[PDB]
Amino acid sequence: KVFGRCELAAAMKRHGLDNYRGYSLGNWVCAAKFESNFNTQATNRNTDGSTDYGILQINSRWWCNDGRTPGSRNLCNIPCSALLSSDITASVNCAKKIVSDGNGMNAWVAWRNRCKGTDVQAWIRGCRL
Ligand SMILES: [Cl-]
Ligand SMILES: [Cl-]
Ligand SMILES: [Cl-]
Ligand SMILES: [Cl-]
Ligand SMILES: [Cl-]
Ligand SMILES: [Cl-]
Ligand SMILES: [Cl-]
Ligand SMILES: [Cl-]
Ligand SMILES: [Cs+]
Ligand SMILES: [Cs+]
Ligand SMILES: [Cs+]
Ligand SMILES: [Cs+]
Ligand SMILES: [Cs+]
Ligand SMILES: [Cs+]
Ligand SMILES: [Cs+]
Image (cartoon, rainbow, N blue to C red; front, side):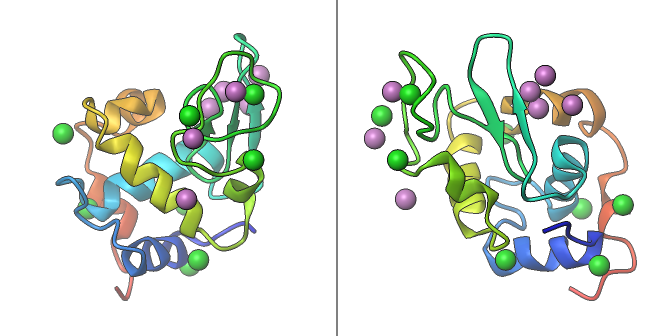
């Protein structure tokens, strides 16, 4: 599923991500825009052999099992395919664990490089939330 910007903002809020660990909803929408262009089915292979899955491009190295990432963990206790669903619940639940891991949203390199410190409220401007 390719979400609309306001559509995704609303889903993320519904799932409790708005201000989770102090990160406003715009931060989450901005990260999804640059991670997946809002497409739940986004996959991207990393140089190390791990793969990133879904709207927030969650990495198999730590967070989900794909069966082909040697020496990895599965700390969200999910198959990585669950992160590609049109329903975002599993991605949001896993992202809550990731953002709580010590480095906040810097866990997402694209958030750090393209969202961090910007007018992230623009990503939710105009949305009925
Ligand atoms: Cl929308
Ligand atoms: Cl957009
Ligand atoms: Cl915001
Ligand atoms: Cl594996
Ligand atoms: Cl594990
Ligand atoms: Cl599995
Ligand atoms: Cl959803
Ligand atoms: Cl933080
Ligand atoms: Cs990647
Ligand atoms: Cs790419
Ligand atoms: Cs790649
Ligand atoms: Cs990525
Ligand atoms: Cs493993
Ligand atoms: Cs596990
Ligand atoms: Cs789970």
